[PDB]
Length: 225
Length: 214
Image (tube, rainbow over all chains, first blue to last red; front, side, top):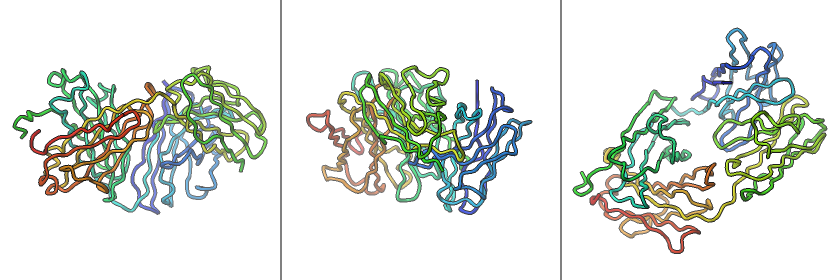
């Protein structure tokens, strides 16, 4: 494979620093010019910085000029971005992208999100969404997971630890008036298999240490309880 | 700086239709211009480089053209997974600049939402705040309205909505409406219902439950 993996992002207070790290595998890193391109929430793609393959030749957008410092270690096949004097607008998801000369960025990472705020981190509460005793649309029954009262973005929800991706709908996070976010993750499954299959939502919030696996199960509903 | 402006900013086309995206550069960039596809929330992908050249593996239905100041991306035979935002970026001169983007939404037939309603969990009832969620699943178009009902009394100002991005397979949308109340305010009432009004529904669908019954 050809892999770029970004890390080092998260919550930082305005004015502080942070170090983004991007590790390359599966392609020749020595001959590739590396780029950083962020995306602000709801906004478009913005190129921030890039670095020549040989290193030592760097370029910066006028936005981050003088603040961000890009570097690479070719012995470690790692691209670095040192972000100093952060502002609110620098909040974004940051991608590292490899490119060869003027031929465009053909290699991309998964992205890492940098939140700039003066609010403290908070971990999510994970609550089950219990499928109803009927749920007859046909053989399809709906069940889900509720992820509430956390900050900052993002959160990662998987079902049965990546084993069930089918019919999974994880909604965008809604910012509440409390200043925290919330979102739900739902999946449709055969109703006849509710008692046979174990359904578990695996939630992960990086800014905290929270990792929760919540078993979702139907109840009696005759006497409730 | 070389400024990139794309047209249109957003469009809707049926599967199989031809869509054309225009990219304009404020200065001559020769042929060095790249098209990127980005699925929502995912990482961008290189489609075209040096304006005419498909990246290896990219579907042939994507075709770039143009030169100098004028550039065009043509998607022939639109496919559902093509729902995404496309960007043009000039490689000719530094600083590198992208275009504003073009959001391409897939046009499909009107589909009615499947409505489920989930009571608050017992665990959440310990937190002094109860949330009841209404699921609108696999509907088109994106426009919908959730009417929340408690003991048939109308509710407003207490609910928030999230809408998923368009599905890459069936081109539908899913929506979640979350009704937030205090635990004491939840325990006083009985019937909780969300009434969904959608274009694909002749009369509104209502899913309901009683607080203690199930």
